[PDB]
Image (spheres, coloured by chain):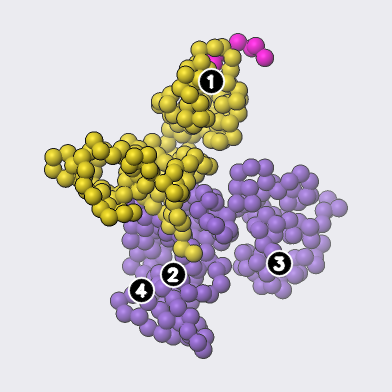
Chain colours: A yellow, B purple
């Protein structure tokens, strides 16, 4: 184990696999302090632990993750329509990481490049983290509590926030918007 | 032919792959009479047609289906529910085949072995063709016209049918139930 491989290359080629663009899309993922992660980028010791979990979590090819040239799978768009989306569960205002969810590109008229599939009470909300702010259902963070709320833009850089509890109004600097719900799947038990 | 191979064991492993607990479910799955399935078990010839379709539909390992060597599934589509579902469009009370839809088995709490993904009025309805008759939202055929209606079982083997312009009641022999909606997806543009 010293075949002359690049750590930063594997760490990035791992990002393409998952389908990331930012390095913050890793630190919290494996629950490590950003400082610990920069260390992984610094030292030449390959993060085999991430390569393995990436191979397991995203299904991406291990051979490719460590070397290759483009023998992973197909994340650029709809492989065969497949399309993987990072998954979560939202319960008691806490967002927890969970299994990736495979879903057809036909579910979205607009490509969902930076999405989240969130399980919350018999429904799976598909969220676009890159959505421009607009009226609609959104995944938000209010003082650390994560929830899905209907937002309505108001003049003066304000928002009306509804759902969960009695509605209220605040400024866009008062709550954090995580992404817009672009689709919802509901089980009919 | 290649002696040793047990047609009985192949058919039972095929049932195992689909998650069927009773032989009648397999007959239903392949649209044959129960007595025809019994003949398949009694005869010496292997059911390669069913094994092949089982492989294709569940992703089960062919070698295992035919010999029992190894294991049914490794990791993906493991046991499952639905990965690729036949797709259709329902418009003007006419149902037309369309391209299949790829969906995660995680969409269904209960396995979905004989499903349909129906695009109707901007939503995608996931239907279980094998569902037992029970109150709920159903894909039905009323004198040839196809629609999705809420059914309520009534005493005397009758049904209350709602969802169209006005509701009506009839016997279970007056309309054809095609399958029960177990999930619905809608884009929230």
For marks 4 and 3, give the CA distance. Answer: 35 Å
State if disc 1 and disc 3 touch (CB < 8 Å).
no
Label whose residue precedes the other's in the sequence (3 or 2): 3
State if disc 3 and disc 4 touch (CB < 8 Å).
no
Dot 1 crowding, Cα within 10 Å, few <14, some 14–19, many 20+:
many
Dot 2 crowding, Cα within 10 Å, few <14, some 14–19, many 20+:
many
For marks 4 and 1, give the CA distance. Answer: 55 Å
Asked if badges 3 and 2 are on one and the same chain, I answer yes
Tell whether position B138 is magenta: no
Query: In which chain is the residue bearing label 2?
Result: B
* Label ID, residue B23: 3
Residue to which mark 1 is pinned: A10
Q: Residue furthest bottom?
A: B156
Apparent side of residue B184 relative to residue A51 in the rendered image (left or right): left
For marks 4 and 2, give the CA distance. Answer: 9 Å
Between A1 and B56, the one lying in front of the other is A1
Spot occupied by residue A164 in the image (x, y as percentages of width and height): 34, 54
Magenta stretch, residue numbers: A1-9
- The image shows residue A141, relative to residue A17, as above or below, that is below
* Label ID, residue B43: none
Q: What is the secondary structure assignment of the residue under circle 1?
A: helix
Q: Residue furthest right?
A: B4
Q: What is the secondary structure assignment of the residue under circle 4?
A: loop
Query: In which chain is the residue bearing label 4?
Result: B
């Amino acid at each position: 184990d010293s075949l002359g491989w690049s750590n930063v290359d594997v760490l990035d080629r791992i990002c393409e696999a998952y389908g990331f663009s930012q390095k913050i899309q890793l630190a919290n993922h494996f629950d490590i302090a950003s400082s610990s992660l920069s260390n992984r980028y610094t030292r030449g010791a390959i993060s085999y632990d991430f390569a393995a979990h990436c191979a397991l979590e995203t299904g991406a090819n291990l051979q490719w993750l460590l070397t290759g040239e483009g023998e992973a799978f197909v994340n650029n768009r709809e492989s065969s329509d497949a399309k993987r989306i990072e998954g979560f569960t939202l319960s008691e205002e806490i967002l927890k990481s969970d299994k990736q969810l495979s879903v057809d590109a036909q579910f979205f008229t607009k490509p969902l490049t930076d999405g989240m599939a969130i399980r919350s009470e018999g429904k799976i909300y598909f969220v676009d983290k890159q959505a421009s702010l607009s009226d609609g259902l959104w995944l938000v963070d209010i003082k650390g509590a994560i929830s899905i709320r209907e937002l309505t833009k108001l003049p003066g850089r304000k928002l009306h926030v509804a759902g969960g509890k009695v509605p209220f109004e605040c400024g866009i600097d008062d709550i954090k918007t995580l992404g817009r719900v672009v689709g919802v799947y509901s089980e009919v038990n």
